[PDB]
Image (cartoon, helix red, strand yellow):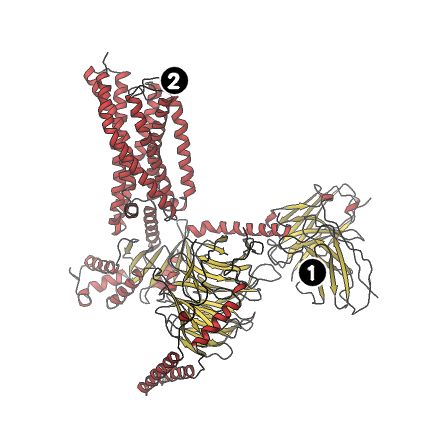
Amino acid sequence: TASIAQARKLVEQLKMEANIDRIKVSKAAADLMAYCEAHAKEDPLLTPVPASENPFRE
Amino acid sequence: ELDQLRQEAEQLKNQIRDARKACADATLSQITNNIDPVGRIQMRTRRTLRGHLAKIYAMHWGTDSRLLVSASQDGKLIIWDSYTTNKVHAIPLRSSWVMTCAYAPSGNYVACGGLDNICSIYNLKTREGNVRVSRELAGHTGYLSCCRFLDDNQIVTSSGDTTCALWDIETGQQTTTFTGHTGDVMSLSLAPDTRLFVSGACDASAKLWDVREGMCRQTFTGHESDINAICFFPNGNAFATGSDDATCRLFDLRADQELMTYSHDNIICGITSVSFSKSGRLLLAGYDDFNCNVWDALKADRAGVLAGHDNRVSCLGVTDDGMAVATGSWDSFLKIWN
Amino acid sequence: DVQLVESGGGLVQPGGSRKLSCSASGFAFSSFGMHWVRQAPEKGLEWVAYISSGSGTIYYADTVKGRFTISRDDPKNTLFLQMTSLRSEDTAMYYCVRSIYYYGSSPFDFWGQGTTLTVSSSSDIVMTQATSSVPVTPGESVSISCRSSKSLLHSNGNTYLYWFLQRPGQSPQLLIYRMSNLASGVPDRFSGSGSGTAFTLTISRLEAEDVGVYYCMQHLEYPLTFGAGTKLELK
Amino acid sequence: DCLFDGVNELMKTLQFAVHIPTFVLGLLLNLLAIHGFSTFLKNRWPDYAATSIYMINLAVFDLLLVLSLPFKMVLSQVQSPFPSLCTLVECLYFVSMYGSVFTRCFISMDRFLAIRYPLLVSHLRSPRKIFGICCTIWVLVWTGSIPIYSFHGKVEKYMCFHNMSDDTWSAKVFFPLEVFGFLLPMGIMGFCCSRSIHILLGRRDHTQDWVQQKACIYSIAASLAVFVVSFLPVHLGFFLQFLVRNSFIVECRAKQSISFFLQLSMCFSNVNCCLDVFCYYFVIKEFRMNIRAH
Amino acid sequence: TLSAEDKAAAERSKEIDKCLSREKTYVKRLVKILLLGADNSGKSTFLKQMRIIGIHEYDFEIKNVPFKMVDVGGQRSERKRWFECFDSVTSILFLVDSSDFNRLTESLNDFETIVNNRVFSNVSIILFLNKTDLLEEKVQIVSIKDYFLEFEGDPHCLRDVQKFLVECFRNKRRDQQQKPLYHHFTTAINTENARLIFRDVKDTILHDNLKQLMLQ
């Protein structure tokens, strides 16, 4: 009954998780670095902004 | 019936593991050696916000990247003008056991929650001039661990009752219960498009949820302990999690498997807070060793040590424009680094 | 709602003394700083005094320094103004103004209907607007302008320029704070912009609540000098 | 007319022999202690801040003492090259030793207050208060040292040594000085240590976990014993010497005996530095493991 | 060089800091006790009597010292962060029904889990063997030997049973170099529990002072 109930919902959950498209990991990593270098120049932590534009200057 | 039920449960487990492995031709570690390394990154305490009487547990950066909200055991929410280290509001919380704080993207609201199992919305822009409680969202049977705003009306809260939920502030009632986790949910990170959100819930598992529907699209395995922090990549289809096994791990939603492991033999304490940089090259993470370590999200090497705290760095956040990083620790101080 | 009612009005002789009491009801009076703006029978607004939250800093206008004393009573929720040795230049109706100060705040938000006192018988930033009784048709687009002697743009990146609307017979209300930000409760038809010194306020539509006298305030220097009266008039 | 010529040369021999190794041993002991408490201040700051501060002050006082010791031995051995240097040696030694004893009295006060009044001390024990008290002790001892040895400096041309190198044998000066240097300090130390030990033993009435403070009791008792051993005989000898010069005169052999015992007691009062390093810092578990390992 | 409005904002921040400093003395002077007990431990009655003279909080004044007893009976979790919210707690008040012999073992297991949590290393444990008269009338009838074979005295002597219970509770404490553990054989109607709790909290603060004094 109830044990059957959550086991039934559980197996449905893994069934739904199974039937999903899976992007290739190499393509995924390539897109990852593509986004990484697309906005690399706009990261203040990556490239310390000059103190003139730095709003936290001391 | 239950025996065969667990039988196809395990069968689906092997099916998904085989699908992931077959889709796993190569690791991000091998594809990253070609590109230039991050080098040495050095940050310094630009401002040291002081005034809190007890240990900080959560901080959230505002959308304007100038205002941040902090929560601590003195039952006080303090909003700081980080540019001029000026306290804007001091909100006396009803319950002193606050464990999460949020800033609305509009900036008109801040939400706090803790052991009271209630996420309380605080209105900052009122005619009376004093921050008042707007709504006490109740219905969770577990301690509030992390709450994030979608709009001024919708807020997603994760609690220790193994169920995240999407609320409706105007009605004050639960809308969709994101059930499926088998353990106490610890952290949440809304997607940049605000249509999905992930959460780690002490089962070494992070589930990606569809906010519109309410079913977890995909569950991520890995990790060996309680996932104490989860952040979302700026691009929108990857997320990094921190646990109690001193390993930060990066997953991808489209590949639904582990990409990299940010683990070092030197550190042995867990990660309390994780947030990416503006472009996501940096993976800042706060550990219990009283300092934060900056990781290169693409190569998994220690890009720098964000030392300067006298106690464990409980919370860690990065501004929307990415021009500063705010770290809160248990020494009742907040330091903004750049 | 938020209310700011003051009391005390009479025909005192020159050289006398009086007390203006302003009662607050509907908001946290302790957190809000209080000002005192006065208007001669037919003239423009002029700043007089200011007391901060907790009675920390107390400023005064040079014309009334020493004679006037402003004290606030937080538990009483009352603002007091001790004036002595009044001259004929003090014949005015005194406006109480609340102003809370933090990042993103809306200073000079709410004004109170003043009480008229009819007395019987430099470093200040000069803000001037060269307009008077602009003939305006209902529904047209107009642009009220104000000028400043010294640039109001500070290094913080925000000009301290304020626009106020004083409807005929009604106390002034805040339209624009810091040259750009819309005040709470005002229509989006009002919009303002400017430069280091040149200032302008443009109104897209002209309905019944817009006819009145406009004002520009500098908040860079505590003398808080106003401008003249534009006096928007229907054509 | 009893003479101390044989006595003073005998001192010139064995007090120098006994000053050599206390000087070296204290030199490296308090160098190590100053380093260790510098560390304890730098990393283990939060709880180990004020106690580190007064131990820093005591260590610096004993370091000044050990720095004054060889200069004192030189001026006792050879004739005074330049008298103001001799009175500088006297002033430095006096200021350092009295600062050490008054800092020890301050430490005993702090320990007794913390044990007897836990709540009030836990509320009112910040590093700033202790730093202020230590500065007060510094200035008090420094402006107290000058008047006492200024008068001796007027007479200090070549005599130096130890016989008359301590103010003047005036009863009007001695009795207030003897009181405020031997009754009040040792009285404070004894009362504080006794009450601290008594309360730590009476904690047995509350807890069965009193036994973990056996080391605490031993450290307090060791502090009291070190103070007594290295402080009582010198002032006792001051007392016999006073009762000989300005009171009943004892025979020549016994007069030489009391002078010799006074000067050996001066050496024992100088070994205060090494005893303090053995007691106040070496009893500390964190010190004796961290600084030993590193 | 700050603007008038920036100066006023700094003034508002100064007032906020002044209010925080005013609250700082009360915050730092306040002692917090995490009250952990069982359903049958008589926690409710002791709590109700003590005040007279989600999770709950009970603020009360003892000898002009701030106090705050935190009850987490309704919501109890075994996760690390839930226990980590009480690491700054001064002492833990553990309530045990000594009279309920059959339930002693589970209370012992709970005590072991609480005191060996590694998040309560810096806190003290004020054990409270409660229902002492129930305990005595059960001891004069029933023997602790049936439920605990390790007991060695006469099971009909009150002092033997009390010492055995205290010894068994103390043995569950793995580390003895940390904060002290305190035991009291008081019932819920002793009306002196406030005095004992104050004495034990003062003893804990004395231990903290001794730790700060480098006396060991």
- Percent of width and height locating residue D12: 24, 22
In the rendered view, would you say D89 is above or below C158? above
Of all chains, the one bearing label 2 is D
User: In the picture, residue C175 is in which quadrant?
Assistant: bottom right
The three-letter code of the residue at mark 1 reads: Ile
The three-letter code of the residue at mark 2 reads: Lys
- Percent of width and height locating residue B94: 48, 61
Mark yes or no: residue C146 visible.
yes
Of all chains, the one bearing label 1 is C
SS under mark 2: helix
User: In the picture, residue A11 is in which quadrant?
Assistant: bottom left
Pick the front one: E136 or E102: E102
In the rendered view, would you say D285 is above or below D267? below
Q: Label 1 neighbourhood size at 10 Å, few (<14), some (14-19), many (20+)?
A: many
Give the residue number, with chain letter if any, for mark 2.
D154
In the rendered view, would you say C65 is above or below B7? above
Give the residue number, with chain letter if any, for mark 1.
C176
Q: Label 2 neighbourhood size at 10 Å, few (<14), some (14-19), many (20+)?
A: few
Mark yes or no: residue E216 visible.
no
Q: Nearer the viewer, mark 2 or mark 1?
A: 2
Classify residue C221 as left or right of residue B261. Answer: right
Q: CA distance from mark 2 to mark 1?
A: 82 Å
Classify residue D134 as left or right of residue E190. Answer: right
Pick the front one: C111 or C174: C174
Pick the front one: D149 or D211: D149
